[PDB]
Image 1 (cartoon, helix red, strand yellow):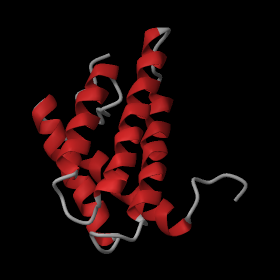
Image 2 (cartoon, helix red, strand yellow; image 1 turned 135 degrees about the vertical axis):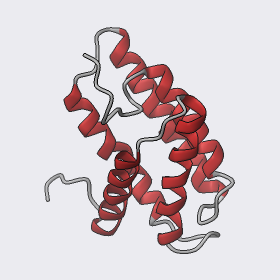
Image 3 (cartoon, helix red, strand yellow; image 1 turned 120 degrees about the horizontal axis):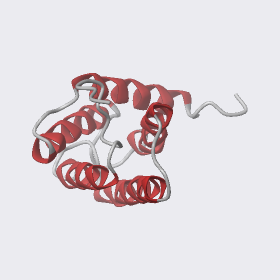
Length: 137
């Protein structure tokens, strides 16, 4: 039904595309990251989008998926955020990630989900320093 809150960018496979594209584009212009790392985030973008593409194509996405995919791509960016190179500390990584998503969602639907951005930045920072996505742990 109509839920005007907690809207996650993975609700629509096309929205995910627009979101992640704008994300990886804008983030490339932000500090902390190096082009070699944006190269991988490009893959993370294409991977997540295609996953949701196939998922929504032959069926649909349940709310449970949103609360899993949010920590999934956070983990794959965590390894990149913890990557040392031209850009500096991880503190500069997560802050840029946060803003990139914000600026992205403004271009796509015009409204940004701040709780989401905070949730993601918590996950990324956590998984990066823990070095795991909770498995065999």
